[PDB]
Image (cartoon, coloured by chain):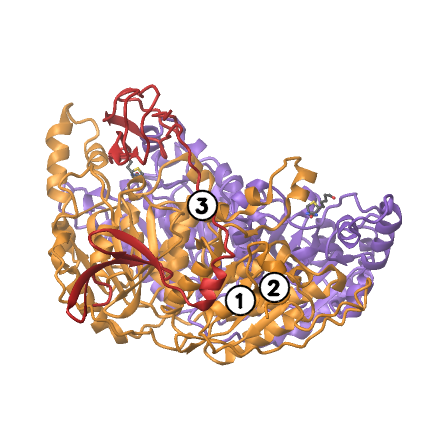
Chain colours: A red, B orange, C purple
């Protein structure tokens, strides 16, 4: 069914079930045996032209993380100078009656000095420094 | 045979003809004019005539529906315009004005052609006038694949949507040489007018793509949404999705605490059909979301706040973004669906020093002037003038709905308690703010006054939206006679 | 009998009724509604009913021509709006929509009335919708005599012109208490939204007056210019001045050096009739002048650059100012006269970081969309896209004129010489820049192409303008059918 997950396919006797995650019209996100892949489905022109396309490399920066917006820090989660893993919440600012929660996108460890509780300073300061 | 394009591809770049071939259907492009020369006769230009004269204009066909397009050529004279280049574009736009067909242009010009004198200015003026006259008649989309400098930048600006390519494109009015000459600062071309700058800082570019191939692939998808002309109806496509699909996950999206945040996409995605959202300006003014989507196989317009970013507070940039989206959607008879969650306007001196009064009025003007069917859903809160601006029932709204835990009040409980009791006995906070929030920060009063049609379970939103949007298919409303409005610029 | 107004005058302030009496004719005001109560029945408001309910609405008559007006009252409840106050204003605006009459309002409200709940929001929404619908049908003028805070600020914004009183008026969206609460900065009310701030920084206020008496006296003079409605013709008044008055002082205004500055008012004043200029926004974006004036007894619109300030360079603020003026002038069929002297656009990073591309397109859109008769005079220079924007002949201009020492070129001589000779032998400056400026920085080439009708002596400008404006009295031009445009916001 269009835009749905389950996809039942049966060649001869063999039967398989795959899943359809999403796409950007050149790359298809399909699941095979409980694993995500990205298959490219392109015609003759797109195939012959995709060779002549720049492939830039994104910035790989392991450095200090700053608070996007002003606020107040009410709760902290991580400890100064210990291990940090991707997807871990680090602290929570509260602004105009709203607690956000900036986390650690991706890294192994940190070296820094924690901003103490109730420090209504923010203004894009260095709350946690990753080194 | 791959002649004369090896020099181009060696620089990791594509050609105009290749871009045109990628955009349209496999074999449905008919180039209109191909043997035209510049006839300049100045500054040693009497030689080196070119057959195509740096432009490729044709008709093409996308998804079985007609289109018109033109593409600049960087190899020939740097893509400069002339008295002769602009004639082809003018002819294409005039033909696409007679017939109800849109126009899409891939800009690559390096600037004006100096060897023609003021004829380049003449051509620019003609193109500007055609864009001005035909805006609101046929949709216009522009993509910038390479450099775009000088006064040629203005014609993409008048167009409805402008997209940018990441690595090898930029746009600005004046070059960095003049900036160094007058101010004395050394800034590179990318640092001045790169795609990121216009994606985040200036708000001109409506999107950014990583490659030309992806740009074409998604431009086709965007084109699948648009109506063909001003008088043609909104397209409807077949779809296996149905209004009876169960959405009970909406009962739990809103947290029971009033100070916790949530993602509005968790409310947007269930209501619309699967994998049918095309966000517009995703990296600019993130506190508001705008884009296109389909509901039961017909394209609609989506405008919702987001408490994830800055508590979902209206601002200057958000106001401009929403105003432009609403104006375009209404110009071509596209239904509008809005989700409301706003505590007010962003407070700060910089805001008044930047003219919040002008900018915030644009969204209100766009919402009030609109005559397309509107549907509004109030999830959690709506305070002060923000409630009025975001498509309130009094602005000729068709149907308005609220969720059982909503709040519609003049302002927060603290300010109301302060103003209602000047020098009342101390500790008044505890036994007054709670009571006032209990009694008047609830949708019961607004429902008593008649400002919301009904209070609904969050699981019935898809059913209600499909029903209302099906019933409202044939509304005919007209404004008083005017030559045109006077919007607060 | 001077009862109950002694308390008001003691604070060096006037009353609403006194302001109304000063505005209209001596005995031609007929108050419409005077015995109306709030019927609230909440928070101990069942008592202290007021007969007028804080508003004075009537009809009046100015210079023998009808008008409609309303005035807030600060003594009664602080001027707060309600479900009942807004009804009178809605009735007045609806009546002034049926009949071709304008509306003028003197705002003094302290904010919304909390004791009514969401009914104040309902009234605000109704007033906003009426302003949105009737903008471009009848002219709307607003004057702010006292405090104006909260969401009530938006209705003056949609109105065509907003004026301010110096000592005792201010306007902003959010009070300084909230600013202190969130940001922590202590700013006074005047430092936040005083008349100077909106006169110079935000660009919202169209003027400032020293006293209420002077405000009324000059508001009458402004009203003498406007047409009564959308369909009524431009007013023409008797005048002893004649087109045959000698103006030979224009032969010497332009200095013979290209780097010396002059005042454009020395060119503006001789052409128009004596003592008939009403500048709009005099203290904001001084590099451009906009206002109203009379030519042979009929009101026209004036838009001219000024090389006195910043070399007469177009900018963001100037673009917004000119765009709003042109849009208003065209909406009501008022002729436009422009004087051109521009070297280009202002170069700087802040400009691109602030969106020059969006703002500079607004003036071009306003000039191209307009259908009223246009007259353009190029005094000294016009370069690049600035020449295109400032009402060039290709944008359906009626008549264009130039002065004998004008210059119309693609860009300055230095840049052209640089681009036309990449690595040409050194010292090329002396024998190339002079030659290029001599050969192509002159109106002869632009006249050969046909972009200026004729090259005239500066002493004939009044004669030519009067002749053309008399002949063009009955032009009928129409744009293609649209629900409305899509201007770059
Ligand atoms: O209570 C003090 C600060 C409350 C601010 C509440 C939000 S912040 C921006 C917006 N402006 C307001 O007046 N309220 C909201
Ligand atoms: O020759 C170097 C500086 C020339 C600037 C000339 C004026 S300044 C602003 C405007 N922008 C230009 O490109 N030219 C004019």
* Residue B282 pos. (x, y %): 38, 51
Q: Secondary structure at mark 3?
A: helix
> Is residue A3 placed above or below B474 in the rendered structure?
above
* Residue C441 pos. (x, y %): 80, 56
Ligand 1 within 8 Å of disc 3? The answer is no
> Mark 2–mark 1 contact, CB under 8 Å?
yes
Q: Nearer the viewer, residue B225 or B459?
A: B225
- Determine crowd level at label 2: few under 14, some 14-19, many 20+ residues with C-alpha closer than 10 A: few
Q: Chain of mark 3?
A: B
Quadrant that contains the N terminus of chain B: bottom right
Q: Nearer the viewer, residue B422 or C185?
A: C185
Q: In the rendered image, which quarter is residue C274 located in?
A: bottom right
**Which label was assigned to residue B240?**
none
Marks 3 and 1, how far apart at CA: 30 Å
Q: Secondary structure at mark 1?
A: helix
- Determine crowd level at label 3: few under 14, some 14-19, many 20+ residues with C-alpha closer than 10 A: some
**Residue position for label 3:** B200
Q: In the rendered image, which quarter is residue C350 located in?
A: top right
Marks 2 and 1, how far apart at CA: 10 Å
Q: Residue at x 68, y 56 (%)?
A: C384
* Residue C226 pos. (x, y %): 53, 61
Q: Earlier in the sequence, mark 3 or mark 2?
A: 2
* Residue B93 pos. (x, y %): 55, 74
**Residue position for label 1:** B18
**Residue position for label 2:** B5
């Amino acid at each position: 069914k269009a835009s749905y997950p389950i996809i039942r396919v049966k060649d001869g006797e063999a039967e398989t079930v795959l899943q359809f995650w999403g796409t950007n019209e050149v790359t298809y996100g399909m699941q095979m045996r409980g694993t995500t892949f990205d298959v490219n489905v392109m015609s003759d022109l797109q195939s012959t032209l995709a060779h002549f396309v720049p492939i830039t490399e994104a910035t790989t920066n392991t450095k200090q993380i700053l608070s996007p917006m002003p606020g107040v820090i009410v709760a902290i989660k991580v400890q100064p100078g210990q291990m940090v893993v991707a997807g871990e919440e680090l602290l929570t600012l509260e602004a105009m009656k709203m607690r956000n929660k900036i986390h650690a996108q991706a890294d192994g460890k940190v070296k820094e000095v924690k901003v103490k509780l109730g420090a209504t300073v923010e203004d894009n300061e260095v709350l946690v420094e990753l080194e | 045979p791959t002649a004369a394009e090896d020099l181009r591809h060696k620089k990791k770049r594509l050609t105009a003809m290749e871009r045109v071939q990628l955009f349209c259907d496999p074999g449905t492009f008919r180039e209109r004019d191909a043997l035209v020369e510049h006839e300049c006769h100045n500054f040693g230009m009497e030689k080196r005539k070119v057959p195509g004269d740096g432009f490729i204009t044709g008709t093409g066909k996308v998804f079985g529906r007609p289109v018109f397009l033109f593409s600049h050529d960087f190899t020939v004279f740097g893509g400069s315009l002339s008295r002769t280049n602009a004639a082809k574009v003018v002819r294409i736009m005039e033909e696409a004005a007679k017939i109800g067909v849109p126009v899409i242009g891939f800009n690559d010009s390096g600037g004006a052609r100096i060897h023609e004198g003021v004829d380049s200015l003449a051509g620019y003026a003609d193109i500007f006038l055609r864009n001005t006259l035909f805006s609101g008649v046929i949709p216009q989309i522009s993509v910038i694949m390479g450099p775009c400098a000088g006064g040629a930048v203005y014609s993409p600006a008048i167009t409805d949507f402008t997209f940018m390519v990441e690595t090898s494109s930029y746009m600005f009015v004046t070059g960095p040489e003049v900036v160094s000459a007058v101010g004395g600062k050394l800034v590179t071309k990318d640092e001045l007018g790169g795609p990121h700058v216009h994606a985040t800082k200036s708000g001109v570019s409506a999107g950014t793509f990583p490659n030309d191939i992806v740009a074409m692939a998604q431009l086709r998808r965007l084109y699948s949404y648009l109506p063909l002309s001003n008088r043609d109806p909104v397209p409807v496509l077949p779809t296996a999705d149905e209004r009876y699909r169960d959405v009970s996950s909406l009962n739990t999206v809103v947290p029971t605490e009033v100070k916790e945040a949530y993602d509005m996409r968790d409310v947007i995605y269930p209501v619309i059909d699967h994998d049918s959202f095309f966000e517009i300006q995703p990296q600019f003014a993130k506190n508001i979301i705008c884009g296109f989507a389909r509901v039961e196989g017909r394209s609609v317009c989506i405008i919702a706040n987001q408490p994830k970013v800055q508590a979902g507070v209206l601002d200057i940039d958000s106001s401009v973004k929403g105003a432009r989206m609403v104006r375009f959607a209404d110009a071509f008879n596209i239904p509008i669906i809005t989700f409301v969650d706003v505590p007010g306007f962003l407070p700060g001196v910089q805001q008044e020093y930047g003219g919040i009064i002008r900018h915030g009025a644009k969204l209100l003007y766009a919402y009030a002037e609109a005559t397309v069917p509107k549907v509004t859903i109030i999830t959690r809160k709506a305070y002060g003038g923000a409630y009025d601006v975001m498509s309130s029932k009094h602005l000729r709204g068709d149907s308005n709905y609220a969720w059982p835990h909503a709040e519609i009040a003049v302002m927060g409980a603290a300010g109301a308690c302060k103003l209602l009791y000047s020098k009342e006995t101390a500790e008044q906070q505890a036994q007054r703010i709670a009571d006032y929030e209990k009694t008047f920060c609830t949708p019961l009063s607004a429902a008593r006054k008649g400002f919301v049609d009904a209070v609904i379970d969050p699981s019935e939103t898809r059913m209600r939206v499909c029903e209302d949007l099906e019933r409202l298919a044939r509304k005919q409303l007209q404004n008083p006679w005017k030559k045109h409005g006077n919007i607060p610029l």
